[PDB]
Amino acid sequence: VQLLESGGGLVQPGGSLRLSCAASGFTFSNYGMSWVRQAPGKGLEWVASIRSGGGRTYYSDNVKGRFTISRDNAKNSLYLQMNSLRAEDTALYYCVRYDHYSGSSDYWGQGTLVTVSSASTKGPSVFPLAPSSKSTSGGTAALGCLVKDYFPQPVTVSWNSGALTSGVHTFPAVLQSSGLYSLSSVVTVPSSSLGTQTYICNVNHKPSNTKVDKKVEPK
Amino acid sequence: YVVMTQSPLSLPVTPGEPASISCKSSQSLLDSDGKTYLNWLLQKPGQSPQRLIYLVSKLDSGVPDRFSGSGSGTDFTLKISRVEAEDVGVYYCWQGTHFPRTFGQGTKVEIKRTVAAPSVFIFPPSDEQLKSGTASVVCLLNNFYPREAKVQWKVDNALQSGNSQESVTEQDSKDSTYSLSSTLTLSKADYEKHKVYACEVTHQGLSSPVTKSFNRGEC
Amino acid sequence: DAEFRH
């Protein structure tokens, strides 16, 4: 069972956005579905639901008349048309399946982030974080990259295109007084494998159509 | 309308030992059909929610039986018989008896593992960022416990304040540690007016604060 | 979830 949401991004207050969720691994038309949202660092709030039968729908008090949930069974897809967006609608929106056999929502997607703001889109600068000269006692150095000055969230980072996961820490973004985010991603590496191993950091900032691959190097 | 109240909101627990989370509803969750629609999910760090329990006490697929749920009417409990590292995250109860769906506030489980000192790294500004009007100095603290850590920047032996930001990872699902990045951001024409850049780290795992610093052409 | 039964 897989639920994959898309369509999130930055929208002006009063603007509109359409979210999609592509389902697979089950007979989509047999299931009720809902959207549930999570404001950054906060809890879970139900948004809207649609039955398997008759296009019957239900909305939370906060979105009545502004959001419309729908489904296209032919395309195994759930939608949320969001109109007259407000700042308080900023959140990660999840597609969620209702399991009639257990009487409970079961599977959640990965979520798509909606940011409602008057601030402008900006893509990040990506910088290598360069191993220190010399310097290290135990034969392990640290490397990373600084992803600086972007808006809105989110940014993703991976290493050697997914090959390199062990030792990787990607920090939560911090919001600067400028209103722009900055984050770092780092990785611990044996001072040994310098000069032989290749470290490429792969940074996506989809809201700005930014997609950078960056190899890192000492001095 | 049906308010779900969880207690405690934060739950530190030593691995191997039991934990218990309370979930109380403002009215009975016994449905007219005889069933009680009380559910539990877990949101692990960096992941989407996953269901643990439905119908009060019924375990979902693949969930280990160290988890159990009990209760009736308005008073419910999730128990973990022996907590493990992988159990870290935020636990939510939600009810499916009354429209609209309502969730509890979430309980964050922290694992109380052994003290672990941070490996500390300082990182000089890249050349690239260092030809674009600004300089970012990065202090990394890797894989430490507990979360409490003091990081202080000193510029030619002068305590800074107001001009840095730090970010901390959530507790690791495998080794139960934290990592922390501190970023000191300076002008080209300020980072060029000093030579001594120091980040001082205080943490319980160290006998005495550790300092890592560099001078500036040599970096 | 109640909406799917009610």
Image (cartoon, rainbow, N blue to C red):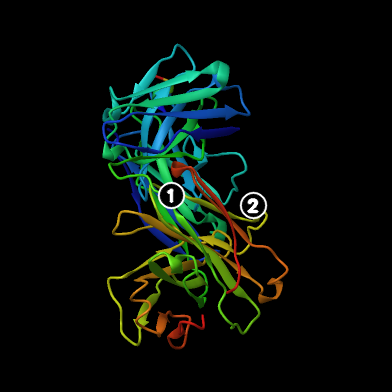
Would you call the spot at circle 2 few (<14 residues within 10 Å), some (14-19), or many (20 or more)? few
**Residue displayed at 41% across by 52% down:** B21
Screen quadrant of the C terminus of chain A: bottom right
Q: Residues within 10 Å of mark 1 (few under 14, many from 20)?
A: many
Q: Earlier in the sequence, mark 1 or mark 2?
A: 1
Which residue appears at 45% of the width and 36% of the height?
A: A94
In the rendered image, which residue does mark 1 sit on?
Answer: A123
Query: Label 1 to label 2, Cα distance in Å?
Result: 22 Å
Q: Against B7, is B188 above or below?
A: below
Residue flagged by tag 1: what amino acid is it?
Gly
Mark 2 is on which residue type?
Answer: Gly
Q: Which mark is residue A156?
A: none
Displayed quadrant of residue B27: top left
* Residue B38 or residue A212, whichever sits in front: A212
Residue A40, given in percent of the width and then of the height, sits at: 37, 48
CB-based contact (under 8 Å), mark 1 and mark 2: no
Q: Is residue B108 visible?
A: yes
Q: Which x, y percent locates residue A10?
A: 37, 39
Q: Who is closer to the viewer here, B154 or A52?
A: B154
Q: Is residue B190 above or below residue B5?
A: below
Residue situated furthest right in the rendering: A196
Q: Secondary structure at mark 2?
A: helix
Q: Position of residue B191 (x, y in %)?
A: 37, 76
Give the SS element for disc 1. loop
The quarter of the image holding the N terminus of chain A is top right
Which residue in the structure is indicated by mark 2?
Answer: A162
On screen, A94 above or below B68?
A: above
